[PDB]
Image (cartoon, rainbow over all chains, first blue to last red; front, side, top):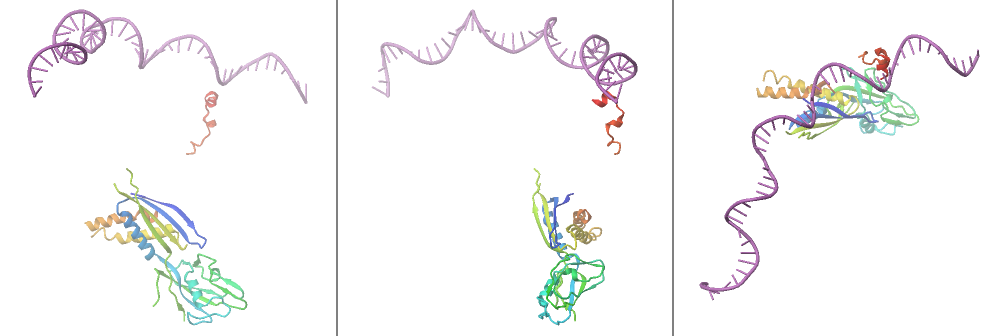
Length: 215
Length: 41
DNA sequence: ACAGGATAAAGAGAGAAATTGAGCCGAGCTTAAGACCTCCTTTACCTTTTCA
């Protein structure tokens, strides 16, 4: 019997949200149990969307250049691996970019479908000079956890909605040994930290439920 | 039964985090129809 | 060390004083209910002003 209270919530400019929760009173040793389980589930067992592959018109390898584009293929790939998207359908989607001329290519230029929302609309991707056309095709998939790899260039997508999890255990002794959990959650903005916390708790409850009524 | 009790404790531990995260009394005393004396006091 | 001698300063003996506490009382004191007299309020109806 405890009470979870969001002490603080923020929305950093990069659209990355932050939250801190105080959970108390917890019995001695339960703070670490809850904190570690929540951290593992949040960072490893939440679903999210990320750019899995990309095709660029004019190149064929990661170590290649694009005439008139300040960055090369590698810089664009790294700038796109951190592009944050959120899909409303379990079906993989394809977005198309075709900016041209002097321009700063940001996330807003990607023509995703109605089912894909770019969390940060101004996310630097490339900088085109005069008489340059950047033709790009991005593929968005549904996955969990950072996933390194072994036509379309395969990418090491970051499916994680949650960016960072920290927890600390204090002592709320009034006058036994009671504990208090302080949980800090940084999310990339695709989910609020309260939605990420709710989904992590749902996964844990679903894991521990069948271990109760039989064995 | 210890495995069952431990699982029950865990489920009860993570349950609160699953989804947690009258017109007559507003009447001004003028409508009480008090005596002018009581009202004024 | 031990014995004798001189002395003053500190105990025992008693009653008489002064307190003292103890019972046994009724005089002082408190409590509660009811009645009961000033002071005040507010009304209903006026009279008495200043003015168009």
